[PDB]
Length: 261
Image (tube, rainbow, N blue to C red; front, side):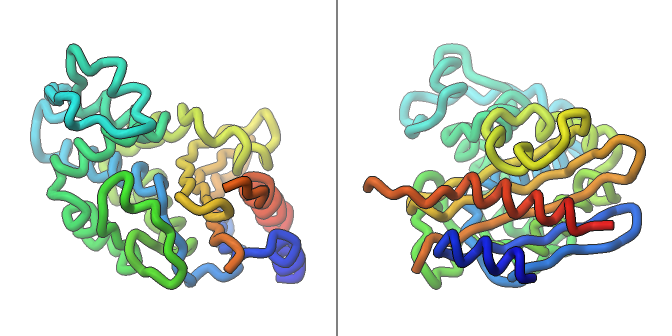
């Protein structure tokens, strides 16, 4: 715990880490049951919920969603570009996962019954910690002590493992989720910064409205041994802030991979 405590003391906020080696069952755990804001990291689980529905509704993924300008919100780079033609459910899911597209996330949330619908999906796979309460952009508020729109590193990692490597999704859906995570573009300074180049990573980041509150979760595939699943979440110390959240996440991920046998 000391390397994590020292990293946390240098950071000035709180860090939470859970890593599980799916080969040996060994774990690394630091503040792993505390709540941290999800921020955009809910969008990965949102895409998984879409894929779960695709087990039961044929054609869902290729179903076009025609949306108007009223659906757009800041930081929606894909959905703004296709505003003229609309986007399918699969295209919105890829945009939400790989570009953190906010309008795409809200459109998919609506499709799934809102924040309550996504929370119910997470309950259905055995996650009792996750809660989504609000939409983009309101869910980013990251008010200290507020349980809205939070989970724990352990619950995130356990749910991620079930959805990417376990039995919570059928194989084709699982592979599509893995592919979306593998193609994420927003995590190049986080967990991916901690891994050897010849491994593979799928991840989803989150960055909240307060500097110092950020996160990343990932499946990491080493060469020649079983994958690692891990989550690293931060809460800001508690305009022109300089909290080095991304470097702390990468450093924590390094310690987790180094600490496993």
